[PDB]
Image (tube, rainbow, N blue to C red):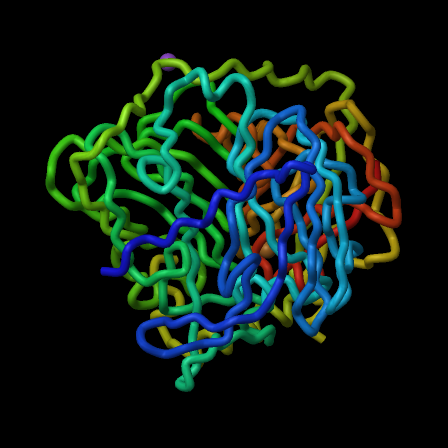
Length: 463
Ligand SMILES: [Cu+2]
Ligand SMILES: [Cu+2]
Ligand code: NA
């Protein structure tokens, strides 16, 4: 098996700057070369390392021949640097943003947010990681040797043409159910192996799929110890046998490497339209882990962090966000799926503006509302009226989930989150915005099934 590629850990220079170049190159997948896009490379991108309380300047060079934007998913930053659809970087052009990092240690990420083209641009290869550290997490003595016992694991599906090229389309089927493929990549590689020291192994898991939800486990059912969600450390580890992960979510887990036997990280079949088609109808390997006897000192602590209590609900502003899809899209989309795959498509169970929030397809010129600054609000996000999956992402914030799709959040989902599950039911988040966003550089809130977002399931808001 190819060894697991490790994104380079990219830190500030002597002048407190970092450079990111967005460009096209070539990658090879199962023998065939394909045109791919990457940050500082051909595919995917580096892990940008930031420290809480320290400002960095990022110089972004768009070396594509089309426009793009750069969104820091999970970062509590002003709208001006948030890199939503209004953050255009012209082809051949350079844009610089200042990130004044002020949030707990977390694994966040970054990716394009081009208006109507976000799905395509991510599918082409654009994504990178953000490793935020603070004064608290380094006290914990977690595994910390980057690319040895502290390893990013970015999992993504793709579909390829006969000629080997990435086979991406925004059409009626994908507008409805998403873009998904038959080939699983792990940091850009197909079924790689990673050499992990005996002791504790830390995985920073990112579901970087456009539309595919995942569910991590191990081939021999050894447990995962969840230590962190989107926006950082949980209060204490949560021990699980499997870990569902929605599109754009991150969890950090420890896994015990307590003998010499190789095992796989795997993903288990999910109940989502289109996602349990072969070979995802069965547990699917993600990467092979090969235990090795080299130095490690990482441990699993009893106690990780202390988070604030949930705010009192009395007197909070309530915002209702109703998600919907044009009936025609739903049936048309389903028709194409059934035509393409047949009964397998339901196993485990103008379209360009057919996806909506509060009866409106995204209008870039009209923020739906102004949210309060520095005050908790309760946002109620409903998917009642359809049975599609919607990982709902709110920019500019790490929030607390009050209810997820009908129930209190699972323990490992009760900490800091930038995404909440909405699937035929209603969710509630308690959300606070510590930074401003004007109408000209508004925050986005949207489904992170990218083809839904691209076809209207998004709103802008100011702070
Ligand atoms: Cu985001
Ligand atoms: Cu959606
Ligand atoms: Na504990």
